[PDB]
Length: 98
DNA sequence: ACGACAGATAATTTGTCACTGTACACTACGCCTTTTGTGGAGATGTCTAATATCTACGTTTTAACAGTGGCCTTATTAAATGACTTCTCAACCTTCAC
Image (cartoon, rainbow, N blue to C red; front, side, top):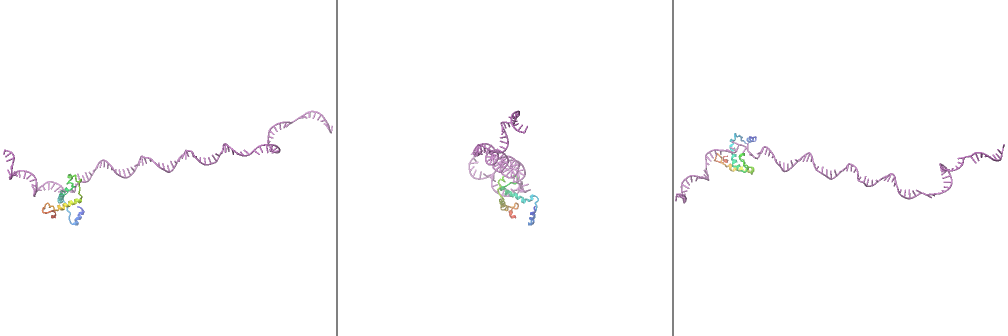
């Protein structure tokens, strides 16, 4: 909702639209669930989905730096997620529907 | 009889795929307590050499004067002066002169 982004809206020509309730966001809410499950849960510093599920070893053996976590996340997107099938088309990857 | 040949047959697991329950909805390493060894003043206590003071130690110097020691010749006679001492301090009578 910032001024700065609205300045970008004017300068690049997109219109900012607000989400009504969180569910309408699901196209971006859900990929956090997808990416948590398929990536972060496998990495040493995993922290669980909630305080009530927080695994106590997370701060005992956190071992990545962000110059590695970037590479992990970028590889996951570009070599897998881009080529993954779009869940309700089936005909083509996520990349080819773009 | 039982059980013993090769093969039937009711399981057992392997693999498909329509279905659904769920998280994504950002929202723990952070709030609070206690101990604790290290550290900064800052009042207070510690305790000396030393440069005197502060008389005395007594020790020199003076002059005053006291005592020792040397020298100093001694006689006679005269004079002047001053003194001392001693002695003395009669009295009636006779005779011849105017």
